Amino acid sequence: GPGSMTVVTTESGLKYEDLTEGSGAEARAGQTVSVHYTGWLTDGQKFDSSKDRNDPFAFVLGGGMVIKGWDEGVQGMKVGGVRRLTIPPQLGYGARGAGGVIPPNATLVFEVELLDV
């Protein structure tokens, strides 16, 4: 209403939006935690959903198997927290893209949800 639909952008260029506040503990650099990522196309079509495959992305805050948006969200989110990270095709898959599912010049959205720390 007063300005909740705001858009944040880091030095990298990516943009994300807070979905829900976590009701547990916050993650810390060097700590291992398990989170779920929900892929979404520019139209809103879910091309990827680890939640459906029960394959939660578990890693330590500070690794190198994720993107700035992920790290940034991990260094602040808490157990049960929900954060939507939106990254462009230039800072995401690349000018090459995946293939049909996620072509170039197409922004991709990912929903990160903290499961446990």
Image (cartoon, rainbow, N blue to C red):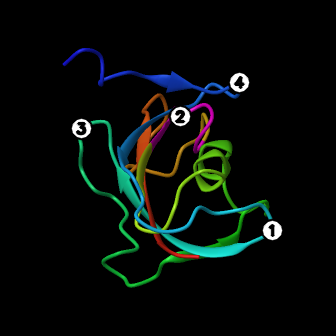
Disc 4 to disc 3, C-alpha distance: 26 Å
Mark 4 or 3, closer to the camera: 4
Label ID, residue 30? 1
Quarter assignment of residue 39: bottom left
- Which callout, 4 or 1, points at the residue further toward the start of the chain? 4
Whether tag 3 and tag 1 are in contact, CB under 8 A, the answer is no
Q: Secondary structure at mark 4?
A: loop
Task: Name which of mark 3 and mark 2 comes first in the sequence.
Answer: 3
Q: Which residue is mark 4?
A: 11
- Marks 3 and 1 sit apart, C-alpha to C-alpha, by 36 Å
Residue at the farthest top position: 2
* Number of other residues with Cα within 10 Å of mark 1, as a class: few under 14, some 14 to 19, many 20 or more: few
Q: Amino acid at mark 4?
A: Glu
- Residue named by callout 3: 43
Location of residue 2 in the rendering, given as x and y in whole percent from the top left corner? 24, 14
Residue for badge 2: 89
Query: Mark 4, residues whose alpha carbon is within 10 Å: few (<14), some, or many (≥20)?
Result: few
- What residue appears at the point 39 percent right and 52 percent down from the top-left corner? 21
Determine the CA span between mark 1 and mark 2. 29 Å
Label 4, label 2: how far apart the Cα atoms are:
17 Å
How far is the residue under mark 3 from the one under mark 2? Answer: 14 Å
Task: State the SS at label 3.
Answer: loop
Quarter of the image that includes the N terminus:
top left
Q: Image height check: is 77 above or below 23? A: above
Range covered by the magenta-colored residues: 85-93
Q: Verify whether residue 70 appears in magenta.
A: no
User: x, y (%) of residue 86?
Assistant: 46, 38
